Amino acid sequence: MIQRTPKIQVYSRHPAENGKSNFLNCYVSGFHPSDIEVDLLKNGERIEKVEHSDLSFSKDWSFYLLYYTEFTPTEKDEYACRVNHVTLSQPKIVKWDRDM
Amino acid sequence: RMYSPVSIA
Amino acid sequence: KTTQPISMDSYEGQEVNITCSHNNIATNDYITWYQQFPSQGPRFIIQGYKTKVTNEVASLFIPADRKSSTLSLPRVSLSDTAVYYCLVGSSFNQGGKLIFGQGTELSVKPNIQNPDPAVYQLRDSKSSDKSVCLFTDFDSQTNVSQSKDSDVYITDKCVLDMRSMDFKSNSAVAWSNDFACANA
Amino acid sequence: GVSQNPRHKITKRGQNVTFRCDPISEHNRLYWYRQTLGQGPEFLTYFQNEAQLEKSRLLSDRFSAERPKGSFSTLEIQRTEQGDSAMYLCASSLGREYGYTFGSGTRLTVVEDLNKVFPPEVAVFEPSEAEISHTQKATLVCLATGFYPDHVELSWWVNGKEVHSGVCTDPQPLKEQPALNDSRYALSSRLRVSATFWQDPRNHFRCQVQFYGLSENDEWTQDRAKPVTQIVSAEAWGRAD
Amino acid sequence: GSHSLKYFHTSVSRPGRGEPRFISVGYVDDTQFVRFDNDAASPRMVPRAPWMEQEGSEYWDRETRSARDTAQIFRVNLRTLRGYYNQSEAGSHTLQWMHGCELGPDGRFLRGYEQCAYDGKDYLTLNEDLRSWTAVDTAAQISEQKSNDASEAEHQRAYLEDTCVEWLHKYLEKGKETLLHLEPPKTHVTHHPISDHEATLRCWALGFYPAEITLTWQQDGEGHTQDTELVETRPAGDGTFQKWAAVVVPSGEEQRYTCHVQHEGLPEPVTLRWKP
């Protein structure tokens, strides 16, 4: 059986201007099998109203979802994406970086 | 418009 | 839309070939064929688009134009006596809902080895008054006639098969409930 | 796979009926067709699980279909007419196309009144000793005298075991009075065997005619014997005459 | 110019937690437009684009039919294979099924394909001719021989070369406002100093459709040029995409680096350089 480890990309919809409504995307790709846990964090705490796209997949049979949520970025407010999958030894957090 | 299988594995 | 011959004869071994009509066959239509044995409901035998397909049961030829399509049975046995339907649709728009023709009644009369056409008479074992006539061992070409008056009853022909020994007899039965045991 | 009950039904024209169909276990599509004599099946309605999808235009609103549990299906014909008399076929498939299997059917006859329904009488007519010499063979005939309607199964029973070699029943039967719409029918069968087999005195030959007719359910206020379902039969031992 | 109508089905078994999970998604080009999920107690094909919102009731009925048919077949195909590969009913397994047609820039039929994958590996794959298969396995070979009859009769052929193409043309016309609007990238270069000796130059493309794009960094003169980190194209979440390309360059040398962007929505391809 194939277990491919996920590829995570955290980013915002639009260029992060402090104090303006934006959207926080987490994009897990390249993973197998389909069962995957993905929470979005504010200051290490879990965000509750987190939507996701419909499970699709790629040419190579790798799954991909987009976990998204409206957020208002601030100078001093940490954001990041937590992903666990049979293929990870522990929940892997990736910090948001407005320059990536 | 999607395709339903006319065969099974 | 699907028109074919209404009925068809054949001899046992004589390879059978029913052909069907559907000028207005859609670009996207499938020639599919069903075989209904007497008493049981119909069952699938073959499907084609354009390539010649072959199976245990039969073959199927489809000419270039696509207007026609010919079902082909080999070494046709008694077994193979059935109604044969020709369908043209796509499961895709239809749903798998089938549209059936009137079909084609196939009959498989036997190659009577040594014809001996007698007309024997049987006494009933319990009530030895009443008696029936048995016209038996005729040549499969023979044209068994319906009746004259009301009170003289004549059955169609009937092939019986003595599997151990071989011999397949044709036989019909006649009776009156004044009546001779000939002239039938 | 595709089973149907009852396999035969009679009803007084005006009464209702409710056949059933059990499709192959996984098949999610179930279809109802309707075959009159020497025709081909007309589609009535099909299902996907419990969902009754399409449903033929011409189909009268006396006819209704049900697949409550998405398994077994019942067809119900209210206030029946002559025309309704047909073989009601059921089919199943795994989605469109794959596994498209039919049932043997439910044969329905609808009658103007139950007094038209008659069981058959059956006699066995022993072999011509004219034949025994000429052919070394011996043709037993069996004769279901006169019955209504054509809901009978004729079986041959040599030494208490059913036999198929040497047998031939009529393709289907004839009308004692072919004018009279609802004539009682008569049916013949043969059973050819070797001379010496018939002449063996310890061989037993039984012609058996199962007749589907009426049940406890059917009320019956005419003098004569109530023409219910039964196996009226007829025997004949081996002799050397 | 290049257009595709693809469809992606995922069946996933759930040992002793109810019957197997099934999901369809359909894409025109890079825009998902439909979805089925049997985990509704009345499962239906639903729209996932605004231009599918005013469709007939028969359209959705006919697609819900196709869908629940596929869920039920694949519910089987999971038991079938579990058998072929002699695996217990404890192991949860995956069937994935993919079928679509591709048109070229010049509008003509490029290729179609129908593809089966069990536990993340190819199983039954339809070939170029749309008539034969390449089964990966002794077990698959069984399922090949069971699928040959249908594809002889050009079941897959006629769907891909004709039906798929016909409906691809329909959907493009239905939603042309968005599907055939070439929204080009908003492109800016950002500067991130690493040390006194270096800085990262990052070239952004933002809010473009379709998702096809080329970000290439170039440097004037003969000197060395460190690998680009090219992040993989990613959705904004509003149906537009994002990509960036980043170079580590020596400090001062920064004005010699120029970033090129090709995309249909751009008349001629653009060059940027970090503007201090």
Image: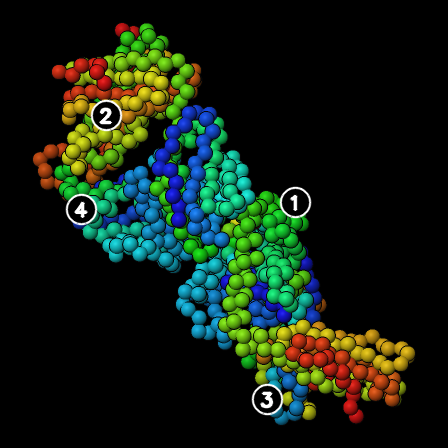
Q: Residue type at mark 3?
A: Ser
Instruction: Using the numbered discs, state the Cα–Cα distance from disc 2 to disc 1 in whole angstroms.
Output: 62 Å
Q: Which residue is mark 2?
A: C146
Quarter in which the N terminus of chain D is drawn? top left
- Front-most of residues D23 and D136: D136
Tag 4–tag 1 contact (CB < 8 Å)? no
Q: Please tell me if label 2 and label 3 are on a single chain.
A: no
**For the residues carrying marks 4 and 3, which lies nearer the camera in this image?**
4
Residue C41, by quadrant, is top left
Label 2 crowd bin: few (<14), some (14–19), many (20+), radius 10 Å: few
Q: Which residue is mark 4?
A: D13
- Front-most of residues E168 and E81: E168
The residue lying at 34 percent from left, 56 percent from top is D55
For disc 4, the chain is D
Q: Secondary structure at mark 4?
A: loop
Q: Which residue is mark 3?
A: A21
